[PDB]
Image (cartoon, rainbow, N blue to C red; front, side, top):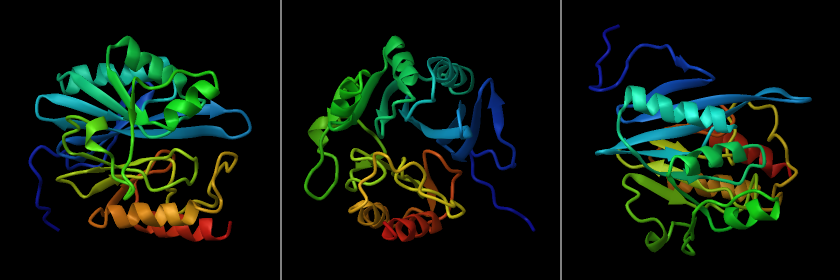
Length: 241
C-alpha cells in the first residue's frame, strides 16, 4: 500500500476552496481551476481551466465564468505561486464567460484565442482576445502566432461542440485539455448542441485523441478530469449525430 511520491505534488486527496473557486493540483506545475455558475433551468454548471507554472511565469488556460471569479484565480496565484501571469489561452468563445476576459485584460494579461473565436465574440457583442492563434493544415498552431508558449501545445481538431474549439497539451506531463469538445465518460449527453457541428464532431474528438496519444489524463471545460475513456465516449455519442 506504500505510495511513491512526486516532488512538488500534493499527494493527498482534497481539493482547495479559495472563495468561489476550487483548485486541484494535477501535476507538480499544473493545477485545475473550477468555478460554478447557476444557469436557469440547469442549476450549477462547472467551468474548468488550467494554471501552468513554467519557469518564472504562470500560463492560464481558460477563465472562470465571471470577472470576480477570475480575479479570485489571480489572487490564488498571488498567494500560492507568486509568479506573474504571462498570458492566457482561451479555448473557445463562451457567451457566459465575458466577465472573465475583462478581468484578465484589466490585469494587463495578454490573451490568445483561435482567430475564429476572435470573430465569434464581437459577432455576439463581446470582446475578442488580444491576439489570434492560427493553425497549420495539420491542426497544430502556427508558431508565429504563439510565441513563448513554453510547454503548451495548442491543437485545433476541427469544429465540434463549437466551430472554434481548440485544445491544449502540456509537454512534460500526461495531461491534455480537451476544452468544450470532450465530455467525461459518465456524461449522459453531449450537452447543449446549439453551436455544434454535427457532421464533424465525432471526427474532431478523435483527432484530439490522435494529437495527444500519450495523454492519459483528460481535462475538460465542463466535466471532472477523466481517463481517455472520455474521448471514446464523446466520439461515440457524437457518432449518433
